[PDB]
Structure formats: C-alpha cells, structure tokens
Amino acid sequence: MKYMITSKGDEKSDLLRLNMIAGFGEYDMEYDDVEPEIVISIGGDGTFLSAFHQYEERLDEIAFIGIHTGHLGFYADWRPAEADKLVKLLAKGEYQKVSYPLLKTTVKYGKEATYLALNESTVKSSGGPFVVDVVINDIHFERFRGDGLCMSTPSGTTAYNKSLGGALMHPSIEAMQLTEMASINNRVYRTIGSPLVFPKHHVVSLQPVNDKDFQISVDHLSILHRDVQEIRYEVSAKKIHFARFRSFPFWRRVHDSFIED
Amino acid sequence: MKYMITSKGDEKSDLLRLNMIAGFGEYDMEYDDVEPEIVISIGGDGTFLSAFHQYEERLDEIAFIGIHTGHLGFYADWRPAEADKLVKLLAKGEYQKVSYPLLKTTVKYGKEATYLALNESTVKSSGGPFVVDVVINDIHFERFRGDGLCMSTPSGTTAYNKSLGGALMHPSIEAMQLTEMASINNRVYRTIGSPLVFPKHHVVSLQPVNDKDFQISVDHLSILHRDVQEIRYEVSAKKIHFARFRSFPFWRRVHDSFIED
Amino acid sequence: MKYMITSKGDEKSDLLRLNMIAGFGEYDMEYDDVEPEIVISIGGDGTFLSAFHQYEERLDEIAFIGIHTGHLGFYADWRPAEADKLVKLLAKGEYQKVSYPLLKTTVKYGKEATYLALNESTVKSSGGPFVVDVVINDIHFERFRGDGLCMSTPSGTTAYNKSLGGALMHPSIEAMQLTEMASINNRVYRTIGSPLVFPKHHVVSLQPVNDKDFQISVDHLSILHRDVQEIRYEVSAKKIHFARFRSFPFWRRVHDSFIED
Amino acid sequence: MKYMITSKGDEKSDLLRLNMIAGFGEYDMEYDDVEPEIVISIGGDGTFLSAFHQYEERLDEIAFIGIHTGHLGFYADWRPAEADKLVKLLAKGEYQKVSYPLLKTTVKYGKEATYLALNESTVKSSGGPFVVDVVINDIHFERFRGDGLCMSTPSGTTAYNKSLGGALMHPSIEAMQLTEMASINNRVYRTIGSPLVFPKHHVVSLQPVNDKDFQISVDHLSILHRDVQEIRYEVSAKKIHFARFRSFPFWRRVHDSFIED
Ligand SMILES: Nc1ncnc2c1ncn2[C@@H]1O[C@H](CN2CC#Cc3nc4c(N)ncnc4n3[C@@H]3O[C@H](CNC(=O)NCCNC(=O)C2)[C@@H](O)[C@H]3O)[C@@H](O)[C@H]1O
Ligand SMILES: Nc1ncnc2c1ncn2[C@@H]1O[C@H](CN2CC#Cc3nc4c(N)ncnc4n3[C@@H]3O[C@H](CNC(=O)NCCNC(=O)C2)[C@@H](O)[C@H]3O)[C@@H](O)[C@H]1O
Ligand SMILES: Nc1ncnc2c1ncn2[C@@H]1O[C@H](CN2CC#Cc3nc4c(N)ncnc4n3[C@@H]3O[C@H](CNC(=O)NCCNC(=O)C2)[C@@H](O)[C@H]3O)[C@@H](O)[C@H]1O
Ligand SMILES: Nc1ncnc2c1ncn2[C@@H]1O[C@H](CN2CC#Cc3nc4c(N)ncnc4n3[C@@H]3O[C@H](CNC(=O)NCCNC(=O)C2)[C@@H](O)[C@H]3O)[C@@H](O)[C@H]1O
C-alpha cells in the first residue's frame, strides 16, 4: 500500500533508502509520507524512535519496520543486506502484525498535556532538589527524594530502565515499570528502592511537595514544565504495530544485544 | 461450610484458634481438616506457607485467610483483635474470592517430580560450583555461573526476590520473575544480570553443564536432587484463592510492610 | 582563641548562635569571622558544607564543630541542648583535633581551575550525551557512557556515593571512590560497573570524546564548564580538622544515621 | 635460590613445569618444596590460591609468581610462552618484591582457630536461618538476617566481593571490605546494605543470636564450625610477597580482566 522511509541522514542510510524506493517502484507501492500504512526506519533505535513520534497520531493505521545501519538496534531488526528481500516480502504483503504496549504520560498545571512513550518517560527537577509524593490508585505510597524517576514500557525495559536496575519484561505483558534514580535513604528519608511493575488500568501519580518545575523526557525528548500540579502514568490504550516476516523472539533479541552476537 | 485452622503452635496462637473454634460452634460451621472449604492460618507468613502446602491438592475448593500474631505478614492480613469480627463475616459468607498466580517447578532425572510454589523456587549446587545453561522456550539464552537462581511468583516478589534486586510485581499479572544470586561476570563469563519477567506459557529450563546434583527449595522446603537432567519453570494453571472481606490493596500492603505502619 | 559561628538562618538557629556568643563573651574569646581559629556551624550538613567552603583557604588554621538543629547531621554531631557545655569545653581548650581527607578536582580548558570537596565532586553533560574516556595514572581504563560520575571523599561515602551503590569508607583511609550514574552496558558499550577506590597519589582523569561542555558540582555547588579538555581527580594534600570533645566513632555515627537512633 | 613449582595437574601445565625445571637446572637453582624462597604456580587463580595456603607459614620467606595456562588469572600474570624469559630473569634475581594485605579470621568456641585469606572469608548458616549481630570495635552495629556475609582483602575485591556489589580496591590500601548476601530489609529487619571498608586495626566481630553452627569458607575452603561463639575479622599483620619483573599495574590488570583484552 502506501509507505514511507525515514533515514538516519548519513551517506550509508540515504543510499539504502534510495535503493529501496527504486525497488518499491517495481511494484504497486506508492510513496506517501502523509498517510502511509508502512513506515520503514533506517538507522538506529533513535531513528526508529523519531519515526514513531512522527506518526504517533496514526498508530492503528501503520506497521513499523526497522533496519539497523550500525549494530543491532532493539527495534531495528533487519540488516541492510536483507533490504532487497524485505522489499519483496513487503510488496506481496500477507505479513503478520505484532503489537507492543505503550505508556501514557499526563501533565497537569494551574491545563493538561499528554505524551505517548515507546521507551520510557522520566522526570527530574529543574535544578533544585527533586521531591515528589508517589500516589498509587489514589493511595499515598511514598515520598521520593533523589535524582528522579523513570517509568518504562515493556520494550523499554532493555533501555534506560535496564541501567537503573529494572527488570527486563516480555512485551506481551501489558504493564509499566517504575525505577528510582539515586534515592536518599537514611533514618529520616526512605523509599521502596525496588522497581515496581504496574498492570493495565493502574494509575501512578506524582505530586510536587515544594518545587513545581520539572524536566520531563519522553523518549529522550526533554521538556521543561513549570507550575506542575500532577504527573500521571498509565499503560496507554494505544499500541504500536510491527510488521514481522520471520521469527525473531524477544529473548533471542535480548541474547544477541547483551550476551553475544 | 467446612473449615479448619492451623496455628503457629505458640501459646498466643493456640488460644486464638480455640476461641475462634468456639465462636464457629455458634453457627452452622463444621470443623473439617480433610476436605475444608475455608483454611485459616494463625501465625506468620511461614505458617501461611505451611497451610498452603498442606492443602495444595484442593486449591480450587479452598479459600485462605491469614491472621498474623506477630507483625504484619504479607499473606496474613488480619489482626488478632479482629478475629471475632472475622468469625462473624465468614459465618455469613457472601465474601469475594481473590486469586493469585502460582509457579510450577518440574524436575526430570535419568522420572519426573513437580512442585507448586506460592513464594518462589530456587536452585543451588550441592556444594560444587553451580553452572547451568538457561534455555528460554528452547532457545539457549545464557550459561549461568554463580551461587544460584530464584524464580518468583508475583506475590513472592516482595520476599526473597526483593532481597536479590528483583522488581515488585502486582499479583494480577500472570507472570514469574527470575533473579540471579552472585553471578560471575568478567571477560570470559557473562550473564544478563537484570531480573527477567516471563509471561504465562513461557518455559524456562535449566540444564546442567557438569555437576548434576542440585539443592532445590520450594517455599523454603529444601530438597537435594541427584542425577538431574532438567529443571523447568512455568506459570502454573492452578491458582490460590483468598477470601477477602474488605479493601486491602496490594500496594497499600507493600507500603505498610516496607515504608511505614 | 578567635572564633565565629554560622547559622542556618531560621529562628531556632539564630537564637542558639546569639546565646552561644553571649556565653563566649564570658571567657577570653574574641568573635572574628576573618581569621577565626574555631568555626561553629549551626544547622544541617548543608550549613556545615557552606562553612567549610567559606574558610577553605585556612583549613590548617581552623577546627570545625557542627551543631545540628534538625535531625542528626553527619558532620554536625552536637545537639542544641549541649551548646552550653560545648561553650565551656571549647573556652578552656585542650581538645584533640581529628583530620579527614579531602578531594581535589582540577579542570583544564583551551587555563586551570581547582576545587576542594568534602563530600564529593560529580560530573554530568550539559544536556547532550555524557561520554568520557577514563584514564587512571595515564592508562586508558574505560569509555564511560551514561548519566555521569561521582568521586567521593571518605566522609562523603555516606552521602551521594551511598545512593549510587558505593561502599562506606572509614575516614582514616586516605582515599577517594568513583561511582557510576546509570551507565550503558550492552554488547557495544561496557564499563566496570563496580565502584573504584583509589589511594593517595593516584590520578583519575576524564577526557571528553565528543561534547566538551560539562556540569561539574563540588559539594552541591554546580558550575557549567565549557571547552573542557580534562578533569583530574586526586586525594588532596589539604585536610579538614575537627575539634572533638568526646568519643563519637564513625561507625556509631553511621549506625545512628542509618540503622536506628 | 631454592624454588618449587605447583601445577594445575593437566597435561599442558605438567609439561610446562617440567620444561621450567629443566631450564632451572642450567643455573644455580635448587628445587626444594619444603623451604623454597620462590614459589611458582602454573594454572589458574585457584591453583595460585592452593600454592598460597600450602606455604602460608613461610610468607615472609617466599615470593610468589603465577603463570596462567587458561585465560588471564588475576594472581597469575604470566603467559606460558614467556616461561623461558621468566626462568632467566628469576635465575639472575635483583627483582623487586610487591606486598598485598591479607585477612585474618578467628573462630572461637566453647578454643580458638585462626585462618589466613588472600581472596575472602565468608560465613553462612549450616542450613537454618543465618542471624548474627555485627559488632565493630565492640560497638553493636546491626543485626544481620540473610544468606551470609563476605569479608574481602583488597586483591579479593575483584573476586566474590565484586559479584556481591562491593567496590574494587587498590591493593596498596591496607583494608578489608564487608559485603552482604541477600539481606532481609522490611519494617522489622534492616541492615546497612552498603559495603563497608575497614582500615587496619579495626575488628569486626560476628556473634550468633540463635543457631551456633556456621559454614565458614576461607578462599573456597569451606569448613563447618559447631558451637561457635564468635567470628572476628581484622587485617592481618602478615603479607604476601610477589616477585615482579615488569610493570603490570593493578588497574591495567583490572581493565584486561573485565573491560577488554
Ligand atoms: N544513562 C543511560 N543509560 C542507558 N540508556 C539510556 C541512558 N539515558 C538514556 N538512555 C536511553 O536512550 C534513549 C534515546 N536515544 C536512542 C535510543 C535507544 C534505545 N532503545 C532501546 C530498547 N528499547 N532496548 C534496548 N536498547 C535500546 N536503545 C539503545 O541505547 C543505546 C544509546 N543510549 C544512550 O543513552 N545515548 C545517550 C542519550 N540517548 C540518545 O541520544 C538517543 C543504543 O545502543 C540504542 O540502540 C532513551 O529513550 C533511553 O532509554
Ligand atoms: N536471604 C533472604 N532474604 C530475604 N528473604 C528470604 C531470604 N531467604 C529466604 N527468604 C524468604 O523466606 C520464605 C520462608 N520463610 C517464611 C516466610 C515468608 C515471607 N513471604 C513474603 C512475601 N510473599 N512478601 C513479603 N514478605 C514475605 N515474607 C517474610 O520474610 C520474613 C522472614 N524471612 C527469612 O528469610 N527467614 C529465614 C529463612 N526463612 C524461613 O525460615 C521461613 C518474614 O518477615 C516474612 O513475613 C522463603 O519463601 C523466602 O522467600
Ligand atoms: N540523589 C541523591 N541521593 C542522596 N544524596 C544526594 C543526592 N544528591 C545530592 N546528595 C548529597 O547532598 C549534598 C548537598 N546538600 C547538603 C548535605 C549533605 C550530607 N552530607 C552527608 C555525609 N557526608 N554523610 C551522610 N549524609 C550526608 N548528608 C545528608 O544528605 C541529606 C540531604 N540530601 C539531598 O540530596 N538533598 C537534595 C540536594 N542536596 C542539597 O540541597 C544540599 C541530609 O540528610 C544530609 O544530612 C551533596 O554533597 C550530596 O552528597
Ligand atoms: N558466586 C560467585 N561469584 C563470583 N566469584 C565467586 C563466587 N563464589 C566464589 N567465587 C570466587 O572463587 C574463589 C575460589 N575459586 C578459584 C579462584 C579465583 C579468583 N580470584 C580472583 C581475584 N582476586 N580477582 C579476580 N578474579 C578472581 N578469580 C576468578 O574467579 C573465577 C572462578 N570463580 C568461581 O566462582 N568458580 C566456582 C567456585 N570457585 C572455585 O571453584 C575456585 C576465575 O575466573 C578466577 O580466575 C573464591 O575465593 C571466590 O572469590
């Protein structure tokens, strides 16, 4: 159907994109980057992230495919040499779609802004000390003092979540995971420490205690928010759809990226 | 209906059991510890664990209730002073049942033995070095060298799993979580490090590399197994049912047990 | 001899300062905040830190004493009710001095600036990704990718170092300790992970790989540095001297601050 | 002078030993495994550990050298191909000696046994729960509940200590480091969590609370001790001496063993 291709912008990725476009010209494939049904990302995981946010308002109409030009990307699971075979299989169709959960961040002021994340959503202070009350389904759970917090999707658990001590979570689990960044823990201040895994329909809310300015980052897009009254986290109802042409299981993907390949 | 009561065995718990029995005599409640429909545990989490394994062959016919005589137990969420009010509400009935996932361990030899866990199932070596290949859905994932491994249920994540760096997982998530015990990690030997969370129908298998003798512990019941060929982990199809009479959410339970109460 | 007193600035601390000054008027004690020999800090650990940096150019001529107005501070080990007994013992003299090691940070450009730390010296990126080569005594040790790094004094190991997984180190050990902040670790990027403890005369140097702008914080005083060519860490030759009037051992101080008091 | 050579016992190591002996026959070198002045270990770190304990009663009269037949050992820093050049340099002499601190474990009963460790000394329970009071210089510091504890030398910090979260410590620092094994931490039971680094002349003592049987392991030599009244740890006055023929710094050794080589 309709398709488009984003590139990292370097020489290698642009040429691959041009060759794939020329290969798509030899089928009934129309290039359309306004209402594509197939979005192809050529680059790394960052490039795939940019492609996701570029089309986040049409997630139900789009299937994503990643090609990695450098080393294996977690979302870009195709080597450049397989691009010709990918063009052919994609042209025919009859591929199966695979869906991963997403995370919804809502920021309220004193107005409401919402964001969608594929990796994670983190919160820090705008300079001063970060102090927030953590409220789970309207129950006050803890007062957090430290560098910040990170709320991860399942496919995000192998990213920033992993470096903060979080657990790696299979993407068929509709959940989100909260991890701490350097929390204070003494006789006066104490947090849970452990990562927390939340199911669908649970709401985690952050409430300022003193400072109301926070730096919020959704998939490394970092925005300063002033006069913040609440940050709410929940598993989104929207999902990202991947076009898959062969078996590449998640735990094998994890093995290749972290153990050996 | 039919019911029975287990006690920690100390003076305080025995007297509470006797008083509850006398209180049950004033209703249409028959004491039966062969085919009870209600099992009451008076003691700590250990006592509740013993009650679970005592009746693990009738989990679908039984609802559990825990009373804690010492401090708050995670499974024993009733104070002794509320025992009279518990007798009354239980006598009427019309309570709602709450189900938690369980973990199935299978041990093969050179014959098959299976176990059911409510907290976790761990594996260590019988003295020599512990070395196992970790296989996920028939895919070889890693070779583990270290002290041992721990596979946790959701309600178990606040137990041994928590002390090994695992994530705390809400019990409505049908999953199991694998955590490492002091793994070797240098240029020659390397593991994933991070905890792993597996959904229903995923099978994690441990395969010996050299030594075939392992000490396997299911809910602190520790058994030596010789001539072991495989240990398989998967989320059980069986579930434990709790009788609940009021709202005591999991994250509030976690807050009380770890933050403050 | 000569003395001065810094206060947190709230009502409670100002009144305590005024009362101690009036008590010092009844001895041969001259108030002098230009060349004091005794510096008294009334507040928390932050107030003590400010007092240290206010007089860092006369460390060999000054002994410090901390009074904590809120909860126990690690450096402020005197309760306000003991202020009168402290005035008396200090007026007589014949107290013993205790010395803690300090950390020297040197920043080079493309010029040289040096800083002295009592808790720690940390480095982050000015927004972009933080990537530095870590060089130990002119040996290239690792390339670090992550949120940042923290170099701690011994008395600092119970502060930020503690929240990043570092070890707690007795202050009689002339050393410094380096800990990571959320490092990337996969098949392509890998760091040591473990904290590193360095003796006197060892030099740890950070060298930029791409971005040359870093946010450097010495005892929570955070400064942006542009066009950075090198950050060098080493145990200082200067030491801070505490006046002590009774036995309050470090591990007891640690017990009171973290286990129970 | 006098010398002897221990081998791992496999074919490769025995032949190397025989060739080195024949090479030593061509100098004024007498083979003597009763009172050697030079001890050569051919194998891995385990083989070097066995050589250390074989001659622990003559540490001041002996210099050690390790040759690694498999991958790089931390104590065995010579490749087999350099054995001929090692024979020659050792025959001449005029080499410089390098000393590493050691750890002294003392076990008291209801009699006294002492052990010397080069890597570490650990303590576990003989089956039941491990519960000990931790006393630092006669000050009660904490009650530990968990799997066990590990007290490490500096050169041991890259071994078991590393896998338990401890810090890596340069061997010129006369110290010992204590790390936890899976400690219980909730509202009722709490430990320090962080590793602890102790200087020379500090004494750490473990005192049983209930069970008095402990499994104590000194450099992987594991002994059951019954009727235990106290386990005392302190930096030994004895030191191990290494013969060094060229610069191979500790942090380079660490880089090669963990980052890349
Ligand atoms: N302190 C920290 N430690 C560890 N990770 C941290 C971190 N701070 C942020 N992040 C993670 O970077 C994401 C944003 N960036 C693109 C990516 C993607 C990714 N997504 C996944 C996934 N789902 N699973 C497995 N690997 C994944 N990756 C892998 O990360 C490696 C690069 N990481 C870097 O940090 N660069 C420096 C700053 N970031 C960027 O400029 C752009 C690449 O190898 C890439 O392939 C965020 O969304 C965070 O998650
Ligand atoms: N090194 C280690 N560190 C941390 N935990 C470890 C551990 N080794 C094993 N275990 C856990 O003990 C369970 C078995 N025992 C009864 C319990 C239950 C429990 N279940 C839950 C739950 N689901 N959620 C939250 N808290 C829970 N608890 C809390 O543990 C505290 C006691 N722990 C102890 O270890 N005693 C010493 C040895 N064990 C026993 O004799 C009996 C009590 O406070 C009890 O209330 C196992 O199944 C493991 O999980
Ligand atoms: N993410 C993080 N997690 C943990 N600590 C972090 C951190 N970021 C920074 N720091 C540490 O704060 C120091 C600077 N601040 C005064 C202090 C002193 C201190 N010194 C010691 C010591 N030597 N030993 C034991 N406790 C000590 N304390 C204890 O820290 C508690 C407050 N901590 C806070 O963070 N406030 C928010 C930001 N900071 C400030 O505004 C002022 C007080 O209880 C105080 O008594 C820095 O130098 C860092 O070390
Ligand atoms: N759960 C655990 N996780 C991590 N380490 C653990 C551990 N349990 C115990 N140990 C450490 O094994 C030592 C005893 N063994 C010889 C060694 C030496 C060593 N010494 C050093 C040093 N100073 N610095 C850096 N590396 C060093 N090594 C490296 O350890 C690798 C093997 N480790 C193994 O465990 N084998 C299984 C059991 N042990 C043995 O049969 C024999 C080899 O690569 C060897 O070269 C102990 O003394 C402990 O320290």
Image (cartoon, coloured by chain):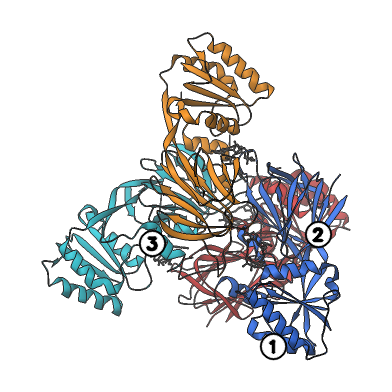
Chain colours: A cyan, B orange, C red, D blue
Query: In which quadrant of the rendered view does residue D194 lie?
Result: bottom right
> Is the C-beta of the residue carrying label 1 under 8 Å from the nearest atom of ligand 4?
no
Whole-percent x, y for residue D17 in the image: 71, 80
Front residue (pair C80, A68)? A68
Front residue (pair B97, C221)? B97
Q: Is residue C47 left or right of residue C217?
A: right
Q: Is the residue under label 1 in contact with that under label 3 (CB below 8 Å)? A: no
> Is the C-beta of the residue carrying label 2 under 8 Å from the nearest atom of ligand 4?
no
Front residue (pair B123, A47)? B123
**Label 3 secondary element:** helix
Q: Is residue B112 left or right of residue C105?
A: left
Q: CA distance from mark 3 to mark 1?
A: 47 Å
Residue placed under numbered mark 3 in the picture: A253
Q: Residue furthest left?
A: A28
- Residue type for callout 1: Asp
Q: Residue furthest front?
A: B110
Q: CA distance from mark 2 to mark 1?
A: 35 Å
Residue placed under numbered mark 1 in the picture: D84
Q: CA distance from mark 3 to mark 2?
A: 47 Å
Question: Where C226 falls versus C80 (above or below)?
Answer: below
The nearer-to-camera label among 3 and 1 is 1
Whole-percent x, y for residue C219 in the image: 62, 62
- Residue type for callout 3: Arg
Residue placed under numbered mark 2 in the picture: D115
